[PDB]
Amino acid sequence: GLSDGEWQQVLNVWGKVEADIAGHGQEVLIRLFTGHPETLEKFDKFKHLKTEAEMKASEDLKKHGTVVLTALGGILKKKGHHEAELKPLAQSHATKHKIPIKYLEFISDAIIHVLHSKHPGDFGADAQGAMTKALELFRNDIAAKYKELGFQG
Ligand code: HEM
């Protein structure tokens, strides 16, 4: 669905995320977890964390922050030819972590909140359009693999 024009857009904005990955990673997860509290319970690793504060204090959260965004960057760099790297993830997210497609919706809303918050004024209408689009693409493909595996429908 995306044009090069757009992918350029997508990879420029990713350059902001890369300057401080554990930084963007931490806030993504915190925003996910606070706005959507039910999501925290899918992690036996973070479930203990009631407060936000307590969350921001967590190096383990930060370290996950970095894994999550290191994996997406990888997909994103691939400009849609990502069957190779998304196959593994759709699998583990479906059958083992048992993460509903709607929680991937949420973190996608989260990546966008976080970029405005942290980049107030240099993440324009075009880049937001492009960022939205590659995150939907990521999502539509997991969705295809969830259907297959017959997980939630
Ligand atoms: C932006 C999309 C996401 C990416 C790229 C991603 C990436 C990853 C990676 C690479 C791992 C470890 C490798 C594996 O176990 O497959 C993982 C583990 C996990 N994911 Fe995700 N994730 C994403 C979204 C989510 C969401 C939205 C949830 C649920 C609310 C979730 C739940 C989990 C859990 C519970 C683990 C296991 C961590 C542990 O126990 O060490 N993931 N994630």
Image: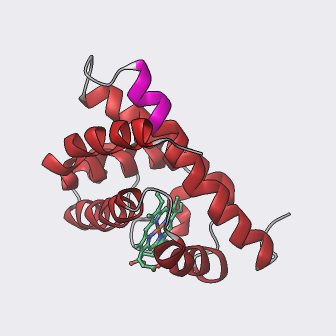
Q: Quadrant of the N terminus?
A: top right
The spot of residue 132 in percent (x, y) is 51, 37
The spot of residue 149 in percent (x, y) is 76, 80
Q: Quadrant of the C terminus?
A: bottom right
Query: Quick check: 114 left or right of 103?
Result: left
Residue 27 versus residue 144 in the image, above or below? above
Locate residue 126: give its quadrant. Answer: top left
Which residue in the rendered view is the most extreme toward the right?
153
The residue nearer to you, when weighing 3 against 46, is 3
Q: Can residue 132 be seen here?
A: yes
The number of discs equals 0
Query: Quick check: 80 left or right of 63?
Result: right
The residue nearer to you, when weighing 137 against 100, is 137
Locate residue 98: give its quadrant. Answer: bottom right
Query: Quick check: 47 left or right of 93?
Result: left
Q: Is 53 part of what is drawn in magenta?
A: no
Query: Quick check: 85 left or right of 74?
Result: right
Q: Main secondary structure of the magenta part?
A: helix
Q: Can residue 35 be seen here?
A: no
| Magenta part of the chain | 125-130
Residue 37 versus residue 42 in the image, above or below? above
Residue in view at x 29 percent, y 64 percent: 70
Q: Is 128 part of what is drawn in magenta?
A: yes
